[PDB]
Amino acid sequence: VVAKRKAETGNPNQIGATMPGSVLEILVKAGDKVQKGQALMVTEAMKMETTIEAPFDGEIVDLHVVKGEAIQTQDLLIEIN
Amino acid sequence: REIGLPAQSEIPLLGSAIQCRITTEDPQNGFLPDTGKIDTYRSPGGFGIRLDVGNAYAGYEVTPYFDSLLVKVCTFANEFS
Image (tube, rainbow over all chains, first blue to last red; front, top):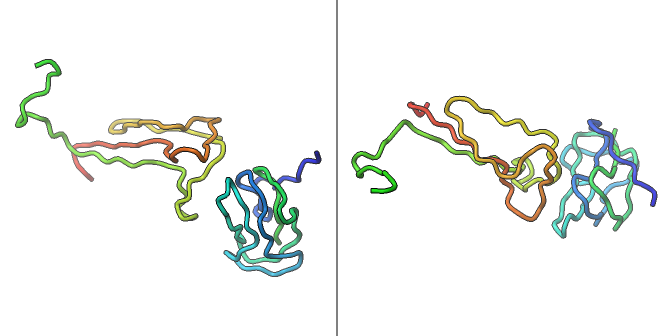
């Protein structure tokens, strides 16, 4: 049961899961350029839907989850530069 | 006679008071109530301050099942300002 890489505390380049749930859709991939507020992925928490937004302008570095993967609070979803 | 309230015209009117409810509603995320563990909870006091606490203490896990209220805060003073 390999533990998932967590998002680093206070590292605003890393987006971690805010609550347990799962990944519905991934809207972006490694390399893309992105803008503050832009949608990056959608996740479910007790069947409510959340859209993960970019914290600022920058370039996606990598994804760390796959479609329909389960996630716990603090799990690292995506890194940005 | 027994509870000790005076007649209507003698019911005191002392200054003014304000109540705010502090909740986990996130005003930058459409007032969606946040959930998760409370790391730190320091409550103020002093003259003119009344607190009626809900569920908020260091270590408490705010769940998605109930309302988002952490604490009710009232202030009171001779003058509204």
